Amino acid sequence: PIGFTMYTTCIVWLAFIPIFFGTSQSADKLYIQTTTLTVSVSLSASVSLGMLYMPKVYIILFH
Amino acid sequence: VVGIAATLFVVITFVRYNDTPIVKASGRELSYVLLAGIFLCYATTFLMIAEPDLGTCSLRRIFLGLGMSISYAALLTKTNRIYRIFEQGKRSVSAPRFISPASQLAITFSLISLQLLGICVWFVVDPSHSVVDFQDQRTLDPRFARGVLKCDISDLSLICLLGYSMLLMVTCTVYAIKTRGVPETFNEAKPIGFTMYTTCIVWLAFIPIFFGTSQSADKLYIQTTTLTVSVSLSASVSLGMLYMPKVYIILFH
Amino acid sequence: SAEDKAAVERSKMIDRNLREDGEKAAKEVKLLLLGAGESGKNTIVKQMKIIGIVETHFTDKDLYFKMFDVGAQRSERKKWIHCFEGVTAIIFCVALSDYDLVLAEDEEMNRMHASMKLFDSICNNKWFTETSIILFLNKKDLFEEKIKRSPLTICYPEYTGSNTYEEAAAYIQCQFEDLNRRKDTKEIYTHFTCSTDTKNVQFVFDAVTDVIIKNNLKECGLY
Amino acid sequence: PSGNYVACGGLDNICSIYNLKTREGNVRVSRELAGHTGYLSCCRFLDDNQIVTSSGDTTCALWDIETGQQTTTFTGHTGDVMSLSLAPDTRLFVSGACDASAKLWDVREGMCRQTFTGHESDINAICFFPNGNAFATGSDDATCRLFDLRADQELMTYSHDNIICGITSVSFSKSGRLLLAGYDDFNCNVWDALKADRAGVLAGHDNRVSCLGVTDDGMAVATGSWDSFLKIWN
């Protein structure tokens, strides 16, 4: 599970380069930039538990 | 063209190497229709790179919608059958309920007919006329001397793709959390879930740059090509995560 | 007429009842038990009962089903298997006390040769091939006792193996697939069924969940 | 024959007798037939009181519902019998076991009167002539023959070169002019009386045919296969 969630985080951060390289010459640059940074850090903090604590919750729900 | 080469190679390997049980574990017609959907998602850009040609706009929108819907429906019915077979064997002896390959093709065609009805309702409410010249975003003050040649079917296609992707990535992930109750060799739960998460994160990272490009001036050419790139890379990663065990066992033999 | 009109409703009701009965019988796995002469025919059914064919029933983890014991029947196999065409699981209870007894007066060989001949005839059959035959090993304690007192290679000159409990219990499995010709559509399951504890039933009951899916996938056609 | 009683077979030696016309009830049981060691194959109703059963231990004895016990016992076949056949005059019945031979049995005295042999393999079902002069018999040797009671021998033989399978059931016509025999090729063949020609060819069966029934009038013939398809041919 650690390797799986790390691979997902690596794919997420690899998808963060084109979104910042393509956006250019726009008056709405900083707004969408901070928005995508905030949602990126939020999803990175969320998948650290959604892909590691799901089996924890499952084995808790067993007994 | 790399995706076309890869899909041709995997189709040749499927039609030539089919006696092994690993390729027979997955649905033959199912894998064929999934490869057809990926090939359609690839040829979307091939048939879109030409002039707008509003009839071609309708053709391209219908083609991309059908490809996306047929790929998602193939994956959904695959995971649903894998999840349902366990309950059918635990609670019944032989309960064929739309399990036969003919019934799978029938339900896939039913989903495609639903998608066609949806896009037909969309065409009925929106005629989608030929809009090639866009003077609202082109500024004549600095003497740009350039003309846009992008079609005007971007917003509706974008919102419909977003909605369908959300619904399918919800239902398929629920089916994938459902299926991993019994272990088997044809357990497509972790790779399918990873592909669904990758597609979801690709869409979630594509929507902000798409909105920023739509808000930018003289950026009507960038949104369409970045949407094409996003769809093509999603289809490519799906084909890769689908064919990785296939090529692995082929190399192992 | 009135009678001809009510006949339609009567037919609808009786067809609904027949469909309900068929749906109720379609969720009950049919087990077909057989074996040699007095090869633990009564000691196996007296296990799950607390927790001329014979009809038995026992429900485990919300799974009710019927089971048919062949009982005592002295007839041929050409006309007896026609009634049992389509059974999903055939449980053979091989005997472990037939290789030591002397040759019978009527049989050309001992009881173990008759047992393997019956197994070959019930396995290498052209009528049922998609079905499956499971093997139950009963009376293991007395078998180990008699194999530690008397050797086993004295009657089987084909191999030169040792005389232990694990090797003897492991060699009897591979000697059953050599007689089968069709292996791509036939399989044989073998499990250990102790006679001292009752908690072994759930050790093989889930094994049924392994084979049933097979014939369920028989409806898929992807194999 | 009167449509009052009905009885089914079974491998557990339980020949439960049932009736149709019952007061305050659809179908009920009154007497229980038991005492057989071999599996029951077929059952025929001689009359409304005396019935005959075919067991798998060479006991094709006659039974009664009132006394619940057998009256006479028929024995003399080296193998078990799996088929029966009654006569229209209700005086005797022919029985043939897997010994490739058929024997006639009387209801009064209860013993074999004549033995007929000539089949290369075991038989499956036997049928009697409506007049009562002979009787046909089908076997797995892809051959058919009708043994005569007076001549003590068969008249003609129905050979087959392109047929490798056998016959699972045989029947006559209304008067015995046309022959019907179901084969293992998921069909049936209609044979002549003396010409031995396949006049009628059957088809349409998805599974193997088990037994066919011909009415007394000889108008239509119903066939029964394993695919749960009771098709009537006319």
Image (spheres, coloured by chain):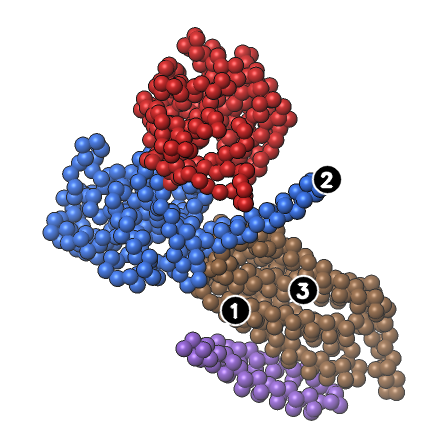
Drawing shade for chain C: blue
Estimate the x, y position of residue A47 in percent, counting from the top left.
53, 82
* Pointer 3 chain: B
Estimate the x, y position of residue C223 in percent, counting from the top left.
49, 51
The answer to which of marks 1 and 3 sits earlier in the sequence is 3
User: Is C175 left, or right, of B25 in this rendering?
Assistant: left
Q: Which chain is red?
A: D
In space, the residues marked 1 and 3 are separated at their CA atoms by 22 Å
The residue at 51%/42% (across/down) is: D27
**Above or below for D155 versus B121:** above
Going by the picture, which residue comes out furthest to the front? D23
| Residue labelled with disc 3 | B69
**Above or below for D191 versus B76:** above
Q: Secondary structure at mark 3?
A: helix
In space, the residues marked 1 and 2 are separated at their CA atoms by 55 Å
Cβ atoms under marks 1 and 3 closer than 8 Å: no
Q: Splitting the image into 4 quarters, where does residue B75 fall?
A: bottom right
Graded by Cα atoms within 10 Å as few (under 14), some (14 to 19) or many (20 or more), the crowding at tag 3 reads: many
Graded by Cα atoms within 10 Å as few (under 14), some (14 to 19) or many (20 or more), the crowding at tag 2 reads: few
The residue at 36%/43% (across/down) is: C53
Q: Which mark is residue C1?
A: 2
| Residue labelled with disc 1 | B178
